[PDB]
Length: 203
Length: 203
Image (cartoon, rainbow over all chains, first blue to last red; front, side):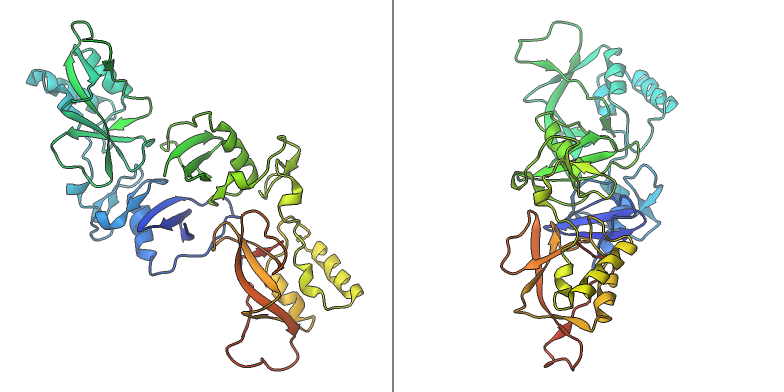
């Protein structure tokens, strides 16, 4: 490991070609500042990711300051190519089986809540929509659909995509499920209903 | 790596038998909580160390909550055996060559400032005392004295001890010096005057 004060209330840890940032703390927290050979990387990092996630900054591609996109709730403009972060709608796939009007009414709905955000939708909300649409999502060791997190298991930042699409950068397969009509008993008993977690998000 | 919310404004990272904590951030920061198999370790950690330092918590020994000692500036009572953290005076050694009255007048003095604290004394202050006492400290590849940091190079938490004493836990030899009268020219030019850093501390 290694660790530097990088301004504006954060600090940044480094080890591998891997890197993290975190808030400073109080005025007693006072490390060496950043080696300037890395001021770049600071700025990049702090501006575009959230604290406490670890990243290989080679795997990502940066573009000029104030002109890109951020994964930070605060931050409207980042330096990430939007091709490269989720757009916050990846959860629609889940409603694929419904009729069109209905997918769309759902989609409207979430924009009626906050949700048509870059983080997607909560999870409780997801579960609950859906429940009501006669669906049900089941943890299927062989399913079509991958659930993912960004960067560390326990993050609140999730995503899903189909098994055969290509992972976005820093996303990491968590598990596999299937979506089916919640109309008949659960098939077997190995099988289980997927509980979207509380405080998770899917975009 | 791995990462959990552990209450009261922090979170904690884990990897190896090694562990760290850091402040949470804003209300958006929301991870999994601690596996309770580790709530202990949280409490231990957050109560006794400062953020952003990494520790092998096996190497340390804990004692009942509210009855021990903390490395945290905030925290009067910790759970560390005081045998096991610095007492904040390790810098006296540096004034070994002066007469007694004079070591003591210096020592009084630092207690006249804040300094007779568990973190010892700043560095600028150290340099500056000493300077004035006709001493001078020189980076001596072969010196008697070890300079140390706790846990990561760039910490502000330093310590020194003689080469032959045993390291306290989590301390890590940084470099070696010697103390001499600042009365005659510097011997050679390989050699250099040690600059105690700004924002470093020695206890």
